[PDB]
Image (cartoon, rainbow, N blue to C red):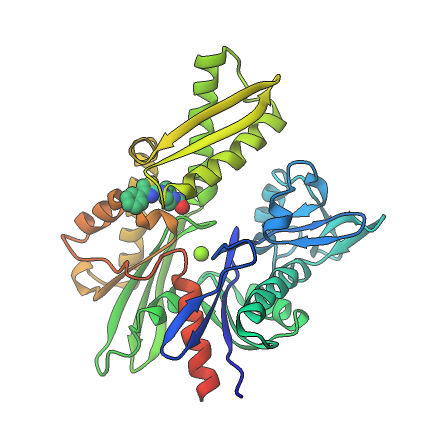
Length: 382
Ligand SMILES: NC(=O)N1CCN(c2nc(-c3ccccc3)cs2)CC1
Ligand SMILES: [Mg+2]
């Protein structure tokens, strides 16, 4: 029997693994039934937890639960991005020769890990999710990275794959993987200008690619760091901080424990809106023992975040300028990230593109892994 290769979207907050088998891509769910797995690792006196198990115990173990390794990978410790991010993380980041390492307690001792070691643990979990589905060990993979990652970040991501025991067939960028998922590199002769609009993940990104005889050229990349998934969560947090003020007469904004528990509920409620018109928030003993039970409607979420959705258009206009292309020169518009599922986000982009239709047939939370899986099958078939 021949071994299939997997495609891995190694995400900032969630990772996704796919495998192409017999003409179709299967996005593989993990052992908790989740088609995406938190890019989290936690350490205890006896265990190293990865994915859902690590994320689900973050509230009581914040110093030894690592996340956001993608924000450190391939960077120098003195990078002002690293220094600003360190102020928000509850886990320790140390400087070892101008390279960051995360330091935690694990098995009764202090241990430090390079970002590519934390990402290799996430990769090992993705590998195991695929091996449980396929029933044999998986070692060939295509791993994706953002188009704006430099050579240091791409090489460090490849190193995480090597540490996880994977043969990294290729490192491809996330917008290229999305275009491959839709087969936009297989439309025959003639160039195709593709715009990839990625909203909902760790960072909002707009990229423009030109595909010519199967060859991809990145013409432009634009975005907004304050349009990541966390900024949508924080908008929901501020809204519920005001609701708790009106209902219980207390201001919880300066209580770290209360704000963190509310942020976890908000992030899950936000995602729950993909399958339901209304998501319930049930937080026991949120602040001073007061239970906070509420809900968020899709209608409210859309109005609350209207300005954030509108803030995505200026980066699209800037990417079109950098690429030296008119809106009418774009053949395909591709949606990536959970927020692109919202018909109001789709309407904003469709109207901006003068009525052009958008590609949304592949679940935007899965499109990057879907494309990485297709590319992995193509390289393994070769
Ligand atoms: N950021 C993120 O992951 N999410 C944002 C909030 N969600 C919403 N989905 C909708 C929605 C979905 C399908 C049909 C109509 C409406 C409305 S608000 C889910 C995705
Ligand atoms: Mg992503």
